[PDB]
Amino acid sequence: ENYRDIALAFLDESADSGTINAWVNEFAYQGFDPKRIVQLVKERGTAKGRDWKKDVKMMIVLNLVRGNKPEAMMKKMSEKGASIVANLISVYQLKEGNPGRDTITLSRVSAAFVPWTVQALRVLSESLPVSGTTMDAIAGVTYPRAMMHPSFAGIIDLDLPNGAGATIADAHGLFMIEFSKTINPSLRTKQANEVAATFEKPNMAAMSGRFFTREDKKKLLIAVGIIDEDLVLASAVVRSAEKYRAKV
Amino acid sequence: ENYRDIALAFLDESADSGTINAWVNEFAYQGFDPKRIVQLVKERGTAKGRDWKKDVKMMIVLNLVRGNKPEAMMKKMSEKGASIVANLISVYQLKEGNPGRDTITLSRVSAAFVPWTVQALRVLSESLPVSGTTMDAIAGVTYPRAMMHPSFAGIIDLDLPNGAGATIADAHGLFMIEFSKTINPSLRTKQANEVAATFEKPNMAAMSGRFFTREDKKKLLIAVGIIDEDLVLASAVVRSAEKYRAKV
Amino acid sequence: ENYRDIALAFLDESADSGTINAWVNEFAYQGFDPKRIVQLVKERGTAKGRDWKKDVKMMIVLNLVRGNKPEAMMKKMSEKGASIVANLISVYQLKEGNPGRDTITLSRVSAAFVPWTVQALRVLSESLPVSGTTMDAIAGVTYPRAMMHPSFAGIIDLDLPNGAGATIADAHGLFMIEFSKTINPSLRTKQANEVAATFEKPNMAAMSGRFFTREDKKKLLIAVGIIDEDLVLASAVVRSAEKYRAKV
Amino acid sequence: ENYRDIALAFLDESADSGTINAWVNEFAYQGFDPKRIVQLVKERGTAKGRDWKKDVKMMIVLNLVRGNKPEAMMKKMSEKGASIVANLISVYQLKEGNPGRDTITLSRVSAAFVPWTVQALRVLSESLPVSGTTMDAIAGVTYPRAMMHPSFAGIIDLDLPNGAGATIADAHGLFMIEFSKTINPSLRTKQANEVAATFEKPNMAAMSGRFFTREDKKKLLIAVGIIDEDLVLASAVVRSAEKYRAKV
Amino acid sequence: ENYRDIALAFLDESADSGTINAWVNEFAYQGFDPKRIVQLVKERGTAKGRDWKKDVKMMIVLNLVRGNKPEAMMKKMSEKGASIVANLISVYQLKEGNPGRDTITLSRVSAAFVPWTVQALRVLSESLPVSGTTMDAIAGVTYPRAMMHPSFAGIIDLDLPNGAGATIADAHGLFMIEFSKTINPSLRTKQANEVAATFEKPNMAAMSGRFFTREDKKKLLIAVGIIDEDLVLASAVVRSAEKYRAKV
Amino acid sequence: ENYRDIALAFLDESADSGTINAWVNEFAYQGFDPKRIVQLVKERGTAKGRDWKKDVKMMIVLNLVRGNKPEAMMKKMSEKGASIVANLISVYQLKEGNPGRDTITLSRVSAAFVPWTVQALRVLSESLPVSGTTMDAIAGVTYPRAMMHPSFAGIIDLDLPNGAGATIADAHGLFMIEFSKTINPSLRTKQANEVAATFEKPNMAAMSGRFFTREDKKKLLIAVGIIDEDLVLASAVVRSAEKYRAKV
Ligand code: NA
Ligand code: NA
Ligand code: NA
Ligand code: NA
Ligand code: NA
Ligand code: NA
C-alpha cells in the first residue's frame, strides 16, 4: 500500500554500460534512414527507363552547391539544361526542408551514397561557396578531400581506438561553420564558438549509425588515402583542428 | 458596525512556526505527483503484456538525453529501433510540455523513479550533452555521479541538520545552468547568475516533498556512497560549489 | 456675452489647504476597498460551515509566497494538500489580476487583514523568495519584521509629525525592488532607481487611506515593538534607508 | 496659353508681415476651444441641480494629479468618495484621450479656467508627482507657483515687449520634461533635450490664443505677484531657465 | 537562327550625350505636375465665387508650418478661424499623403506657385519650426530668404555654367535635414550625412523640370537679389555649404 | 539483400573534372534567360508598328537609374514625357520584382543587350546615383566605362587564362556595394565586406553563361578598349581592386 519502498527500491538496480549504450543508440529516432532511400530509389530508377546511378550523380553534384530545395527551379540561366532535372523530380517526389523520413531529400541522397559524393567532391571543392583558396587562408596546411561535405560526417566513428575520430569531428566542424556562415542569413556579430549547438546534434547523430559497420568506415577513410593502415592521423586534420581547439 | 476594530484586532494572533510551515508545504500545488504515476504506470504495465520496469528503464535512458518531447519521433536513423517506443507511448499517452498533472511526462518518470535513474546515469554521464570532460574543465575535482540530473534534485533536503543540503542545491545548480545553456535557444550574452530565477522554483519545489521521508533520502545519498554515515560532505560538492558562490 | 471676464475672474478664488486636501484624498478612486471585503468574506464564511479566520490564515500564508493567481493550481506536488483550497476558492470566487474592486484578490486579503499577516510573516520571512540572509547581505543591520510585505505599506502614514513615515516609505521601498526583481521577468539591465515609478502609485495610495485612523496605525507599529511610545524610529529602518537614499 | 508667365508672375506679390501673421494665427485649427466649454458647462451646471463652479473645482484638483482619463474609476480606495464623480461625468460626457474638440476633457477644464487652477495649485504643488522638494533639488532658487501646470502655459505671450515670455516658455518647459518623465512609460535612456519636440507644438499653440487679450494675461501674471508692474522678471524663472539653456 | 550575333552586335551603336540626356529627363515620371494644378485650380477658383489667388495665399502660408495634411483639422484653438479652410478644401478635394498626381497637395500648391511662396516666406521664416535664430546658430552668416522651403528647390538648375547651382543644392540641403529633424519621429541617434538618401531623389527631381526655362529661374534668383547679374554667388550660400561639405 | 556493399561500393567511381563541371554549369537553373527575351521582344516589336531597338534603348536608359519597377509610374514631373512608356509596357507586360523567367524585367533587357547598354552608359555614368566624381573619390585612378552596371557582370569570364576575370569580379564588385548602398534601405552600421553574400550568387551566375562564347566576351572587352590584344589588364581595374582586397 506504500509507494515509497518501491520508489526507493529502484536504487539497487544492476547497471551495465553495454546494455544502456546499446539500447540508447537505436533510440536515436527515425528522422532520416539511408537504407530506405536506396530501396525506393532503386525501384524508381529500375522501373523508369533511366539509370538511377547516372541520374543520382547529377542530383548529388547539384546538391553540394545548389542547396536542398530545387523547387524554385530558377536562377539566371537558359532553359534546356535545367529541364532534365524535372523528370527526376517527378519520380522522386523530392520535398523542401524536412517533411518526412520516407520523403527523400538530396542531402540524404548525398549521405546514403556519400562515397560517390567524396569521389565527385574533389574537383568541385573549389567550386563550392568555400573556395579551396579561402580555405587555404583559414588553414595553412593542405586540405583533406573527403572531410569537406557536412553530410560526409556520418562515416567517421568517434568510438574508434585512440579517439582519432573525435579530433575529426572537431576538425571537420570548422568547415561547417564557414558553410553555415555563407548560408546562414545573419553573420556580422555571430560567434563561431557558440553557433556550434545548431547542427551539432545532427552531426553527432551522423557519428553513430547502424547503417555502416566500423570496417566499412575504415574502408572509405583508407580509400581516400588520408589515413594509413597503421591508423596514423593525417597532419592536416589535427593541424586544422588546432584553430578550433584554441578558439573554441 | 465598525470594520476597523476587527481589522486591527487580527494583530494579536498567536503565531507558531510549525503550523504555518506545515501547512505552507502542502500548499505547494498539484503540478506533478510522483505517487499517481507509479499507480497508473503499474496498472498499465500489468494489464499490457510487457514488463513496466524493463520499458521504464528504456524510457528514462531516452529521457535524459532525448528531451521531454518524443512526438517528433524523428532524428536521422533507421526504423526498427525507434519502433518499440510507440507501443509504450500509446498505453502511456505521453504529452508534450506540461498539459496536466495526471498526464505523464518522461521527466516525471525519471523523478518518481530517480534512484533507478542515478543507477543508469553513471555510464551515460559522458553521453549527455555535458560531457564528463567539459565538466572536469568546469570543476577540477572529480564529479558526483548522482547530483547530475536536474530531476535528481528532489531527493535532497535543505532542512537537514548543518544545512549540507543547502550547499548541494547550489552545487547541483551549476550543472543545470550548463544544461540550460545547451537546451536554451539563446546563450551568447546571457549570464549564469541571473538565469537562476528560471528553473529555481521547480528546483525548490523538488527540495520539499511529502513523497519521501528524510530516511529515504538519506538511504539514496549514502547508497551512492558520496556521503558517509558521519554525514561528512564530499569534497566534490562543496569544492564545485565554490565556483558558483564566488561567481554568484 | 463675454467669456473672458469670467474666465479671468476665477483667479481671485479663496483657496484653503484643508478643503482641496480633504477632497483630493477621497478622490483616490475605487480600485480596492478593504471594508467591502471584510463584510462579504464574513457573510461567506458564516454561511458556509467553515471558519473564515482559519481559512483566511491559510489564504494569506499562501498569498505571500505563491503569488496572486492560484487558478493554475499546479506546481510539482501530491494532490490532497492542494485540495482544501478549492472549497475556499468556490465561495470566494477569486479572480486573476485585477478585474474588479468587488472581486477579491488574496493580496487584498492580506492588506485588509494586514496585522494578522505581519503576525504570520515573521517565521516565513526567510521562506519568502527574499531570504532573511540575502537581506542581511543587502543591509548589515537586523531586519524589521513588519515592514516586509509590499501590502504592509498601507498602515504607515507619511503625514505623521516629524515625517518618520516618509523614511519608512523609502526604507520599505527597497524590499519591493528586490521582490519585483524576483517576480519581474527581465532583470539584467534594469535599474533599481528608475523602476520605482511602477508600483510607486499603489504604494502612495496605500499610504493614504480612510480605512484606518492614525491611532490604529500607531497601535500596529508599537505592537511590533519597532517604534517606542516616544516615537523614536528604529535604527534598522533609517539605516536600511541610507542605501536607497545614496543610490537613489 | 502659357502657364509659365503667371507661375513666375506670382513673385512680385506685395508682402506685409501683419497680414500673413494675423491670418496664420487663426489658422491654428480647431482641436481645443476654451470658449465652447464655458458655454456648455454653464448650461449643464445650470440645468442640473448642482453648482458648476463647486463641481469644476473638484474636477480640476482631480485633473492635476489623477491624469486625463477617469473612466477606469479604480485605484485602491473606499467607495463613497469616488461616487460623487459619476454624477458629474454623466452630464459632462467626458471622453478619454482626444476624440473631439466639442468633447470636453478635464485638462481643457483646467486650461479654460486656468486662473482658478493656479489658485488651487499652490498647496497641491508638493502633492503632485513632482514634489516641491525634488523640484528644489532640480533648481536651487524658490519655485514659481503659477508656472507649474503644463496647461498653465496658454496665458503667457511670447510676443510681449523685451521677450520675457520667451524665457518663461523655456523656463516652464523643464517642469514638463520631469512630469513627462513620470507619466512617460520609458525613461532610462531618454534625453531631456530631444524629447522637447513632443508636447512642444501644443505648448506653442497655447502661447498664441485668440481667447485672451494681452491685458488679461498681464492681470494673471501680476496677480500671482511673480512679476511687478515695471515688468521685471522674477529671478526664479530665468535662474531656473539657465539649467535648460546650458543643457539644451 | 543565332541570338548571339545580334546580341553582341548592339555594341557598335552610335551614342550621343544629347539624345539620351534629353530623353532621360522627360522619363522622370508623372508623380507631380505643376502645370495641371494651375489649370484645375484656375477653373475651380473662377467657377466658385472666391478669388483663387487670395485663397491660395492662405493655403500656402498654412502649408509651410502646418504640414501637408489638414484633414485632422484640429489643434487647440477657437472655431471661426479654421472654418474658412473647409470651403477651400471641398472644391479642391485635397488628399493626405501622395495618392495621385492629379490630386492636389498643398506642397504642390507651394511648388507650382513658389515665387509667391518666397514672397510670403520672409516674415514667417522665424515663424517656421526652424527659427531664424537657431539657424543663425547653425550658420554664422546671415540667411538666404528664398532657399528656405524644401519645395523651393525646384527652381535652381544644377546645369548652369560654373555649377553654382550644385553648391546651392548642397547648401539648401542642410535646412532640409533640420526640418526633417523636426518632423521625423526619431532623431536621437540619426546622422545628418546618411539621412540624405531619403528626400534626395525628389530634390534632384525638383532640380530638373520641363516646367520652367532657365531664364525663368534666373529671374526668380535675381529677383530675391541674392545673386547679381554677373552671377556671383552670395557668400551666405557657399559659406553655409562649408558645414555640410566638411561634415558630409 | 545487403544495402551496405553497394552503399560503400559507390566509392570507387571514376571521377573526371570535365564531366561534373560541364554538367554543373547547365544545372544553374532557369531564373533568367537572355535568349528567350530577344525572340519574344523581336516578335512583339515586329508585330507592333514601332521599332523594338529604338524603344529598347529608351527602356534601358530608363532602367539604369529608374530602378526595376516602373508600375508606380510617378515621380514629380509633367505628363506627356512619361506617356510614351505605357505603349511599350502593355505589349511587353513587364512585371515588378522577379515573378517568372518568361516575364521580362528591364534589367534582363539591359543584360541580354548589355553591349548597347555599355554604349549608352558612358554619358550617364555621372548621371547615375553614383556620380563619376564620388567614384573618383573612392578610387584615385580614372574609371572603367563598361564595368559600371551590375548587369554588365555577365560578359566577363573568370575561367580565362591568367585569371584576369577573377580580378574584374572583385574590382567590379565595389561599385555594386555603393549602388547597393544607395538602394538598400539601411546603411548606417552595415559593412561592405559582409554584405557581399547578397547579390554575390547572381553575380557568379552571371560570370558563367551558355549564352556567349568566350570570343564574344573578348570582343566586347577589347571593343571598349580597356584591354589590349596582348590581354594586359587595365591599371584601373586592378588598382581599384586593391581597395577591396585590402578592406575585404
Ligand atoms: Na529552343
Ligand atoms: Na525492413
Ligand atoms: Na488517494
Ligand atoms: Na456603505
Ligand atoms: Na459663435
Ligand atoms: Na496637354
Image (cartoon, coloured by chain):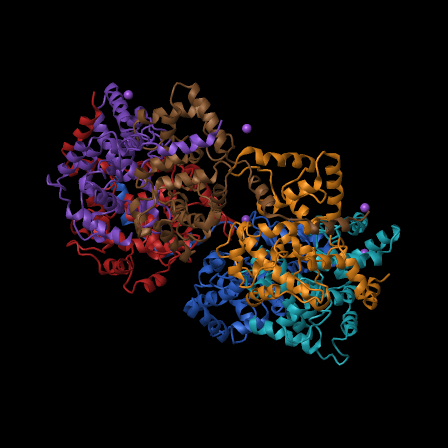
Chain colours: A brown, B orange, C cyan, D blue, E red, F purple
Choose between C148 and A86: the one closer to the eye.
Answer: A86
Is residue C235 shown above or below B116?
A: below
Residue F160 shown left or right of residue E66 in the figure? left
Is residue F39 shown above or below C114?
A: above
Residue B205 shown left or right of residue F113 in the figure? right
- Rendering coords of residue C41 (x, y %): 82, 54
Ligand 4's image quarter is bottom right
- Rendering coords of residue B168 (x, y %): 64, 62
Residue E239, by quadrant, is bottom left
Q: Is residue E207 visible?
A: no
Choose between B234 and B99: the one closer to the eye.
Answer: B234
Residue C200, by quadrant, is bottom right
- Rendering coords of residue D246 (x, y %): 42, 70
Choose between B64 and B81: the one closer to the eye.
Answer: B81
Extreme residue in the bottom direction: C230
Extreme residue in the front direction: A230
Choose between E178 and C43: the one closer to the eye.
Answer: C43
Tag count in the figure? 0
Q: Is residue A1 visible?
A: yes
Name the residue at 36% across, 41% down: E52
**Which quadrant is the C terminus of chain D positioned in?**
bottom left
**Which quadrant is the N terminus of chain D positioned in?**
top left
Residue A124 shown left or right of residue B93 in the figure? left
- Rendering coords of residue D236 (x, y %): 50, 74
